[PDB]
Image (cartoon, rainbow, N blue to C red):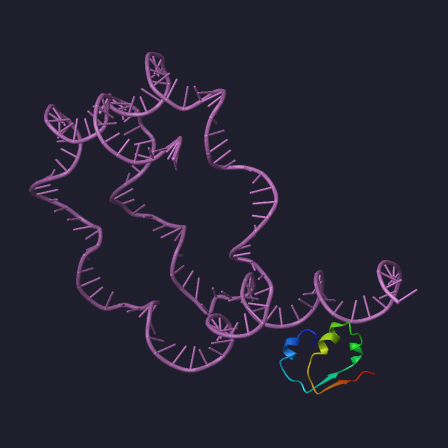
Length: 48
DNA sequence: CAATATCCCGAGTACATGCACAGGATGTATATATCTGACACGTGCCTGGAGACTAGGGAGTAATCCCCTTGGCGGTTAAAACGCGGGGGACAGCGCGTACGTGCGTTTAAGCGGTGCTAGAGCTGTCTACGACCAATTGAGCGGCCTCGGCA
């Protein structure tokens, strides 16, 4: 998802389930910077 | 405007060329010749046509920055022109090779009969090479942990 961004930007996803979202913990990360830009109703984090 | 240069015209200039000549070797001229291959005849093949279908490619577009393109760059010599050196240029002869002629004799072409080499045969009869797929490796980029320099 941090590479095929161009393809994911092509469609209006209803929701993102970001499983084990502790992966996103640092704002310095490209992952975080890019994952902010996708458009959806809800962003759902399932991180224990 | 001045200057070096190219252009242009007439005098005077060896020999080059076009010609006439003798004469020799070859192009002609006739008769003969078989055989090349022209021509005629079928043989059988591929060149072509004609269909159905996928999938590969081709064409198109979109985004864009690489590369080309341009300007302006700063740096150094080919050109210009002269001075200046020796070297390319024009005659005397030797004899050695080249030609050419003679008689040098080696080999080829031809026609002979015999015969084994090669080149079209196979499904030969496989199985190298041809896909098909799998697996390893390196490299690169992205997270993550950790000392230290400049700032409160």
